[PDB]
Image (spheres, coloured by chain):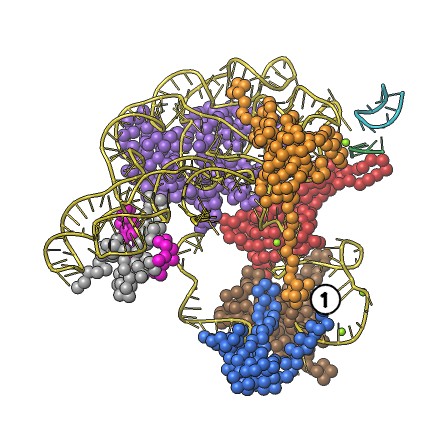
Chain colours: A brown, B blue, C purple, D red, E orange, G cyan, H green, I yellow
Amino acid sequence: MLTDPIADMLTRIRNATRVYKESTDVPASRFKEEILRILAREGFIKGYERVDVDGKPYLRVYLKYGPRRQGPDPRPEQVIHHIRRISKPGRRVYVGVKEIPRVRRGLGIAILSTSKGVLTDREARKLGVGGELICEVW
Amino acid sequence: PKKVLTGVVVSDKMQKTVTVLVERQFPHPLYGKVIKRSKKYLAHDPEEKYKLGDVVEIIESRPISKRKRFRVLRLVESGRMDLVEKYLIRRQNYESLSK
Amino acid sequence: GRYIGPVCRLCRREGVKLYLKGERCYSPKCAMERRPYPPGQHGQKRARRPSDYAVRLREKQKLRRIYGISERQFRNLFEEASKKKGVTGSVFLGLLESRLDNVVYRLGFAVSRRQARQLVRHGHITVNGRRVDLPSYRVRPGDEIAVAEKSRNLELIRQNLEAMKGRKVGPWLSLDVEGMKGKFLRLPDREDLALPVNEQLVIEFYSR
Amino acid sequence: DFEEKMILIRRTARMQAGGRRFRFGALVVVGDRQGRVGLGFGKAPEVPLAVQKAGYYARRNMVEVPLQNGTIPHEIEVEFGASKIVLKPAAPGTGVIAGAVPRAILELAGVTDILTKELGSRNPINIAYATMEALRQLRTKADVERLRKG
Amino acid sequence: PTINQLVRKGREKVRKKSKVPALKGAPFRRGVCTVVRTVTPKKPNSALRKVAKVRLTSGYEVTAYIPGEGHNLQEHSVVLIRGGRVKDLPGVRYHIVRGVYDAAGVKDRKKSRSKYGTKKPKEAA
Amino acid sequence: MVKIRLARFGSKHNPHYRIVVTDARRKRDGKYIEKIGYYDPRKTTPDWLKVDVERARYWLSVGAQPTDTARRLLRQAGVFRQE
RNA sequence: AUUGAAAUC
RNA sequence: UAGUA
RNA sequence: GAGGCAGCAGUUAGGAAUCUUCCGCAAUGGGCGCAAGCCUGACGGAGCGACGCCGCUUGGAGGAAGAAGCCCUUCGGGGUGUAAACUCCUGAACCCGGGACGAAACCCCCGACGAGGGGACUGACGGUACCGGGGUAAUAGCGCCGGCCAACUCCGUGCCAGCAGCCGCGGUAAUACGGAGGGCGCGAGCGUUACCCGGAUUCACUGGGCGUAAAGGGCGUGUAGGCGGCCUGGGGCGUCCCAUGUGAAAGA
Ligand SMILES: [Mg+2]
Ligand SMILES: [Mg+2]
Ligand SMILES: [Mg+2]
Ligand SMILES: [Mg+2]
Ligand SMILES: [Mg+2]
């Protein structure tokens, strides 16, 4: 049926970015929109925007890459190196402010859903809340 | 505080008494997943007032019997023959689990 | 109890002159002058590329053999320094350097750590008046490590206190020469000693 | 110039018509101990040309090691084949705590404070190669600022 | 396995078993000798290797090995056993301890004197 | 009956007591209801005796007989001294 | 005796 | 036939 | 008929193995007594075990281009080795002298049977600790040296005798066996056997896998169970946050 929408998305982005595509549709939800803002705000993507495709709501996603590169294999470095579900339908992961992960001594995100709303780790830490630990990007 | 549990009546086939199934969910001590677990409690019903499919609160009490230690505090909602049915199959399932 | 046996003999084997025999291991021989090589039938034989273990070992032997202390005692001191706040190798050199039997020798009341030990056991040395006969005693900073008034007379105390009339003393120490007493001002920094031993190989020796 | 250490030398063997026929494999690292190391695995009829050959290759094969006071920016894991290396930053006083192979690469890069585990197949060649990829792949606040900027 | 599976079945603990029933753990056990055969080994080896069968205070009857140069053991000898495989002798999982009971030390033994059980000598000593 | 009294801590030839309240029937070094001081009979320290005296008064107030030597020490820090 | 042996004289 | 590259 | 040490000692038996039929109620605690006191193998001590942890001794400084002996030797030499000898120095042990804290209460006297003041009795450890005086060069062993793992040579022995944690050493030139010399490691210890966690991400939550390496059920149907698309609203069980209670002492 489509068991995890959030993961599907996290993956559509993993997959597209690895053949250096410019854009990617994902079928649209509010919670999906949210994660994308944090993604955009921390400059892992250029951004997103709604659309309609065959009568139906998608969110186009504008990926972003490094500069073309030197020697044999000139493929760019990649702005999103690592994106990964953590809470999952078959095993939900919840953490309190005291146990929030510090992805990659600082250089990394951990998107994280709380009662104050969807938030990065430092956001959440400073707001002092924890929650369902959605995923991590670096 | 005297514990208050809420469940469903799954038997009133006993005089002044009801079997009340009570579920409960939690993180698993090692493996994360939220699991469910459930328990019948025999709760006292002096006015044989509650019946099949009532969802009821349940309270810690001074012992009424061997294994009655709770009293039906109040009705939460009537109906719920689904939950009762859900139970009752799981019970009749055990019939072709033997040798 | 402690080593006891042939010595300027690892003023050999460890490859570098250890100061162990004091006035002679200074004057055409810590035999290292006459024989700069390992002891025994195979001493001057073609050297063998040695293991990253053999290397690490030797180094800790070296350090331990300088101060004359045992492996049991040494190993503990080290353990104590890992659990202690701060960069660990230095600290250990610190604690190692704060042992009476060695401060006494750093002040030149004796010419040898071996000799300086015997002065501590045998009574002749004090810590702020009170007499102290444990070579292992942790001199802290502000202490006064004196000679025994009843021991000043001794030929050996005099002869040795005498050669210190001119001589200079460690930056973390001082020395009133005619009052036959000195002072542990602070614990030394790695920089302050010039020890023939890379300390980080010691840490590494005890990480397996 | 650099300082150059030999990790490993091995003798291999092809089989030929009556008799076996040896050959020698050499793993060498070179470093200035200030965030430039290189690895070379060179092979030949006799050991010294293997070693010498290794040396040459190792200098053709150098890396950006972004030190941060005797340690590294962050943690990496790398799987190279069924060889996994895990690398962790440590405070001063810690040391280089690894097995021969990554120690000698890390020491000569100019690291003094790191935590590691050799995981999976511990084959030295493949472990060595993994450590390098691991190094080759570290970043710093500067680089990720730059990347995420646009 | 899926987490649900792990929640249903768990992982199973690994329990490896004793390489040596000298029963009750016991670091040693008392024997009375029974037979003092001589055994030929295996694999790529040959030599006549000294052995005893031993009735144990465990109720066990087992083949143990007499180490050292020569020995003084026979049908009623009475030995201590420490366990220690041989390797060349399949089914030989224990050793006789030289120097306790009617097992002799080892005469004229100068090097590994502590094993083999032989007191310090008095030559130029 | 509940007691204020001395429990032996320290080591051998190093007595050190803790002035404790406890049920009389408990062993000496067993579970006490409340610490209320300590005491070093060799006075090897400048501070060889100490007593939380507001607390001592509390228990006395709810009936707790002290050992005889518990009460000596209690006195030294004037538990019973008035006005 | 033959190769270190087993076999064999 | 056994040990042995 | 009598009896019941899984109280303290101690005897026996099983067992690889586990102590004195000890001193004292002086201290703390307990019971009865108004008190003096009586009882307490609780306890406080001593005795035996290197059984564990910590401290310390068996010397210190001089001392040959280097004794003797013993080991190597391409017969020149090399090693043990500043090690001994021997020169001065200090003075563990041992002898003499003095000598504790642990104990101030209860009790008695003043006061009032209170508060406060005064006073006396009491030490099993013990003539011990500690202080002063005198004063003798005065114990070293165990494991290891093929690789992993730190340390090599000569004899002996010939798939024998034997070693061996694992790979494996021994068939007349053995750094792997046995002895020598020498060397390495620990040192009043050093080895061995057993058992536990480790390394073992080798039950993998952190942290594993299944085409051919161990591993996809012979296929469906579907019961329970696990899991569940987009939007809005109510509840607040899961989840998060703040206060507060609990979390004994010992341990870390
Ligand atoms: Mg064979
Ligand atoms: Mg041996
Ligand atoms: Mg494990
Ligand atoms: Mg199939
Ligand atoms: Mg189906």
Q: Chain of mark 1?
A: A
The residue labelled by disc 1 is A19
Residue drawn 65% across the image and 66% down it: E8
Amino acid at dot 1: Val
Q: Which residue is at the front of the view, I248 or C147?
A: I248
State left or right for residue E109 relative to residue H3.
left
Majority SS type along the magenta span: loop
State left or right for residue F3 relative to residue C92.
left
Q: Which residue is at the front of the view, D54 or E101?
A: E101
Residue drawn 65% across the image and 36% down it: E54
Residue drawn 53% across the image and 27% down it: C36
Q: Which residue is at the front of the view, C80 or E22?
A: E22
Specify whether residue F48 is painted magenta.
yes
Q: Quadrant of residue I176?
A: top right
Residue A52 screen position, x and y as percent: 69, 82
Q: Which residue is at the front of the view, A52 or I202?
A: I202
Write the start and end of the magenta stretch as one range.
F25-51
State left or right for residue C42 relative to residue D22.
left
For the N terminus of chain B, the image quarter is bottom left
Q: Quadrant of residue C127?
A: top left
Q: Looking at the picture, does residue I156 appear above or below residue A26?
A: above
Q: Quadrant of ligand 4?
A: bottom right
Q: Quadrant of residue A117?
A: bottom right
